[PDB]
Image (cartoon, helix red, strand yellow):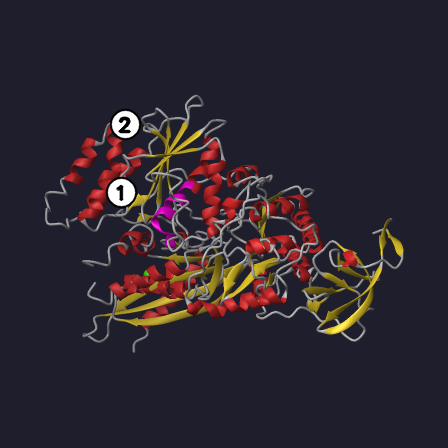
Amino acid sequence: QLLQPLPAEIKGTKLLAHWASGATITCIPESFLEDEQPIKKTLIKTEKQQNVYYVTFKVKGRKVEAEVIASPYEYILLSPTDVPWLTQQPLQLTILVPLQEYQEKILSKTALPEDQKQQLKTLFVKYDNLWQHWENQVGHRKIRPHNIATGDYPPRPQKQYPINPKAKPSIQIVIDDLLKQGVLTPQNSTMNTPVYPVPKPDGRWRMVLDYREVNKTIPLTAAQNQHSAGILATIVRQKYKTTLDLANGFWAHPITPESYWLTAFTWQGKQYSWTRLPQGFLNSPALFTADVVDLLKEIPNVQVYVDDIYLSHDDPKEHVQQLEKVFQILLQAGYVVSLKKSEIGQKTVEFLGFNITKEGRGLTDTFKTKLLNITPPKDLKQLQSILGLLNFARNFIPNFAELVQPLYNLIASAKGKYIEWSEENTKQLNMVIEALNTASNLEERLPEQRLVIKVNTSPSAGYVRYYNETGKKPIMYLNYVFSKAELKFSMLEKLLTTMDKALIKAMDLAMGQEILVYSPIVSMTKIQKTPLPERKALPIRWITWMTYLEDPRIQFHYDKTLPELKHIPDVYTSSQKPVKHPSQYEGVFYTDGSAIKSPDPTKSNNAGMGIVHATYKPEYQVLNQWSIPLGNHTAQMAEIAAVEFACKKALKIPGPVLVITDSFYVAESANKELPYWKSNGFVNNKPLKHISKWKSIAECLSMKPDITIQHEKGHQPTNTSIHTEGNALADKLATQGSYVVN
Ligand SMILES: [Ca+2]
């Protein structure tokens, strides 16, 4: 539990003891007492009567004799009374996590009224014991331990090859912390399981076990938790959502002693074994998620997957009241919550098990139908790929042959490898896509036919078509918006990610029917065999991906007709059309620029920018201002140069920010041609200083995209809104900055 464990021998063999608190006597695990003859017998209520003994054992090598009782558990529950010389100390592991930053970040990113927010701040110190305070700190379920030596045919010990030593240091800490708490034991065994390293985002390495041999030895004879698609249709959607990360909760369940060998692995020649459920093993995920779902069966609105728990309510009092019941259940069960990834009391939870943030209030989530604009090719190979991509539409889009003539009129005309795109060609590409998005080329879902899904993927996005089985038009397309990490996946993994995404929206359209999936992969047998140096996706991904092959209402098929897409340009997303309120953010950055005639004939011009940091929380308040003289530059470059400054000053703000511009050019260009200018390389602008001014709002939005940019005219504006006050302030500053001369 949460006292330092204590290392001991009884009869030759070593074992762990946990300091006790009750007035009960010292329980020994039941298999040591078997040969010992009983002293008296005595009825324990919490009235099962039991034999009592008097035995000798060691604690830190020193000998103890004690009046003891039998325990079905794996450890010694040690009475403080029996050991008056030793004192109880708390658990000491290697690296103390920054629980304070974690808690501050969660109190920050919260939609709770500061009233309940303050009640959460008291809850963080109410069951502080149920929070992960140390790295590698595991919990301890006091449950009946599991037996995974099922199936009589043993697996065959896999040899352990050498691995990267540059990872051994950060992995040894883990090994030593999981020994100290008894999660590993040093037990030479008949099985050897292979081990590999994978890099962690922080620059350390985390260890992976390749259990694919053991797993074919044991059967999935167990009531599996509902799968991703089962959970995502059932979930309640109400105002306040919350997700909690069990820190490797499967490590909390123990396994029987006769099972330790099965889990064995070698690390620096010494062959260790697991006291607890291992990650990789066939039945871990379902046994742990089973127990979780039992523990929260009384809670109205809860969904669990792997170790991620999501709970949501409408009434902010009832949310935190239910959440305390959960904290109690998890504490008394021995579980351990990690607040680094956890998200409490938020109107949008960044992920509820799968890769999809939750928002608003319906029982089912609801995603954007239409796909996004592709950017222009930079190459012949990039043009041929998109051609071969659109080729399927000839048969159901009447205005295709014409639309596409100009693009082909681009293959042979500039027959010199690289071609040339006019700006009107990009307008024709957008016209192409809009056709496919018009409701006359979209079929309707037919409950008699089966539901067909055609899946491919570029490097930038996944491409998904939905058809009816015999249909000639697609019900709806669906493009995929890869997360920052999803981008790091290999190709085939991009295809499988996209499959999970597509099947979540699909679980709505099938409406009691079957689903057929067509893809460029020849088998769903050969792919489980893909070697682990190639899997660039966490095996949580590969698991969630392969849970779908146990569903009878889903079949996978190889479509030879599909085009090779490893040469599609970038998709052009947009933070545009979601223009939102003026005041609901966490900060507002007004911007302006002026330029006037120059006093020295040589410079010819003279510009100044202006910037305002205001927050519109309870009411308008100004946090800082700025009036910066720029030199001889375009007035439009003052208005441009001001938003770069306020974007850079925003990276310091963990939250949503708003940036206001007088300049239609900047405010539109930062919405319509910026995603384009990026995938162009700033070619044929403008000498060099001009180009080195646009790139930096690019890079600054890349790093933080939760920053929006609006526009306004603002001429002769008396009080045209509540919003123009700030932009008059900012126009005063940029004009002030203009008049000053160096
Ligand atoms: Ca102006």
Residue 492 in magenta? yes
Considering every residue shown, the one lying at the far bottom of the view is 742
**Whole-percent x and y of residue 421?**
18, 48
**Whole-percent x and y of residue 727?**
41, 59
Under mark 2, the amino acid is Phe
Lower position in the chain sequence, tag 1 or tag 2 = 2
Q: Which residue is mark 2?
A: 396
For mark 2, give the secondary structure.
Answer: loop
For mark 1, give the secondary structure.
Answer: loop
| Residue sitting at x 47%, y 39% | 548
* Quarter residue 533 falls in: bottom left
Report crowding for label 2: few under 14, some 14 to 19, many 20 or more residues within 10 A (C-alpha).
Answer: some
Query: In the drawing, what numbered circle is on residue 170?
Result: none
How far is the residue under mark 1 from the one under mark 2? 22 Å
Against 322, residue 76 (above or below) is: below
**Whole-percent x and y of residue 413?**
10, 44
Q: Which residue is mark 1?
A: 564
In this orientation, which residue lies closer to the viewer: 148 or 390?
148
In this orientation, which residue lies closer to the viewer: 3 or 96?
3
Residue 637 in magenta? no
Ligand 1: which quarter? bottom left
Q: Which residues are magenta?
A: 487-499
